Length: 330
Image (cartoon, rainbow, N blue to C red):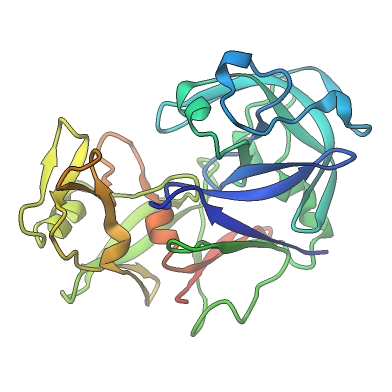
């Protein structure tokens, strides 16, 4: 089997992407944030504290003939940005782009933090990291991909995120029309439960490529590109007036600037992030100071190839017995 679903930016800055997901019988369609950096499929629901719901579509398990309470199971998750959610667990039928999993753990939120409440466009998350990170207790649950895997034509999914445009998540096949040139594959470590890999270096604009190992994670649920301070300093040094602002929380630059591209290495291959992808617009409405899309990972504890990087590529998440990641230009 295969599935194919369109993913759409939630706003004009590509802050996140939502993908429609069918849950239950009859189907309840919720727009979920597919997150290769976490491993819980959780939804706003009829159980979510009412004051914490502001415009989201909710899952109502009592209206699904295939929903079953997973007795005794609870979940609680905190994300890298400090947001969080928690609740209890149902199993139900879940379909993405025509690919159906029965008995999927659907984690029903009783509580969500303010960032989730304030984002009316995101009805929940669908985690696509390794199932070892799943937070359900006392019995850890599998991700949608892990459950689907044995049925898939090939044990893969691909992320093809758009720049200010829709894109695609495919499951079970590689669309050879969706990228240019070849796919370069690179090793993955699952030791931390992430799609963790090592980039072979970087370039700033038309500058020479610096060969250097950068360990990081491919994370569709993170907006920006977080890299070591040395790398990020080298990038912003090429932008007149750019500076790191502790008050704002990162690198800012004059909105009048033209930003250079940023290249990252995948083996001997190179992925180029256009400068426009790195402009995240005014820090506040009407400001002429703009927020950078490449930021330091210092004090995050890990480098993160978030949407800024991933949307410049066609990305293969290969969940074979030995997992790998593939990147192609597009």
